[PDB]
Image (tube, one colour):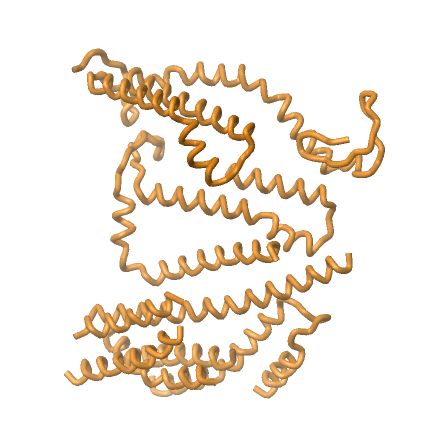
Length: 303
Length: 149
């Protein structure tokens, strides 16, 4: 911990250096924060495994929650709110662990009401995702009075996901700022360009967040099944050498629409990303840059 | 109605499918709709595209004729399929005509490939003096299709 604190202090001292700006500074800060939070998680794991499968569930849940808490700590009023949320979220983990394997229902309802009251000031201050998440706990508390436990588990997993997504938001914003400063210095030596790369990163992060959301929310597949069972028209395709009538569905139609929109967005936001990546790293002639841009455009639209 | 039948393909099996008065009326309706859309094309295009965004008259005419061509082609294809259904019969003629009539794009694709090769190899740069075909001058802009001197 002493060496970790010394490294963190050195990184804080060397913050926003013009001659030492790099995209690795944010990853180093994230690693330092993770290392700082690691001792508390290790202590929690040791406490859980001191007497040792009921206890494994609480040990794992507490370790994960404390790791998230340490990540938030190492990265004012928000700190106090995060500290206070521990008592509100403690009984949820116990209920989830119990359900994995009279007064309890009242305690759960009181905890949900307290969580809603705590989140109400945040909703008043606040965009739509936070309000939707806050409203979901109220509906879960109303419907609780077994599946509500799984709904609450999905909700807290989604909360962890959006927290991680916002952390990555800040990280990519810092990286984009560093890259923009570097390209500005290079241009001086020799915001639409940065905006195109920002949009590409936004699309990539939205895709990753949606993939994670589908990974956690694997229970509600009825909508996907309905979209994949439209059966509009069929064509005689080949399957293992056999002529089988495969029918296209609304899922296939939506997939085609999404692919076309993604291709159009990639085509429109191509030159900014190419100039940020290839031109900045290695200088090249304008003619060669134009030729490679048009080659990429052609192959992308063709595919 | 079951007027006449043709040996079509269903799940890899040769099945005699018979056209009906319903198919004939569908073909007639499709042809009439295609004709009406062709006749009432430029007004709709000027109301929608021209009003929202200003464009050159030449570009508007080109897009109008492109839309007309694709619409009449798709209408003829639908009419032929809904009455004859012989795509698997005239696909060979389509391919032969396709090559015989797409040997018209050689002069364009050669231009594009030559432009790409010139851009990659850089035999001439912007600012020098070039003479070709008794046309001496300073090259100003270089593109993938044509070069300006």
